[PDB]
Image (tube, rainbow, N blue to C red; front, side, top):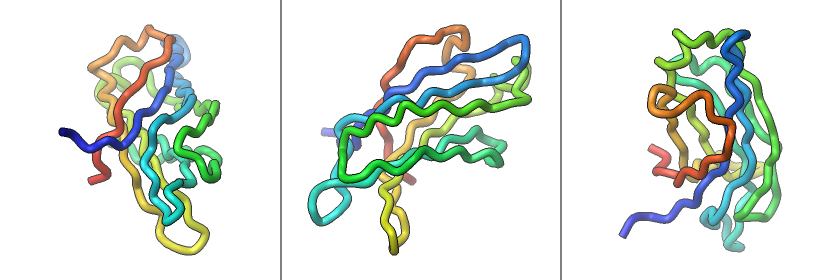
Amino acid sequence: HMVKLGKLQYSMDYDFQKGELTVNVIQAADLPGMDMSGTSDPYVKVYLMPDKKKKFETKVHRKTLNPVFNESFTFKNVPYADITGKTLIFAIYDFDRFSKHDQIGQVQVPMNSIDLGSVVEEWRDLTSPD
């Protein structure tokens, strides 16, 4: 029996001519409750490894384990020769006004393991923060 951390739905729109990757953070489902009340205040950070310079962040959603983000971010200067060596990371956090934001889990997508020409949605299970 594997730990259940929820799942994330995203989609990607890669522009091969301009070398630009648009990432759509659509929604998360079945997140665990991080707070005493059994709920969370989720948000997502998005970045590309090994760059880890551009770190996009979604708005913070309040008191929900099934947030619908519908946010889009565009990475630039990622021509085809460059993007396939990178790994896209979604890191999901529980916001807290005062304390450190606890990481719930993460989704790692090696860019060489998918079809960059696909624009339809994908669900991925969250794995452990590490």
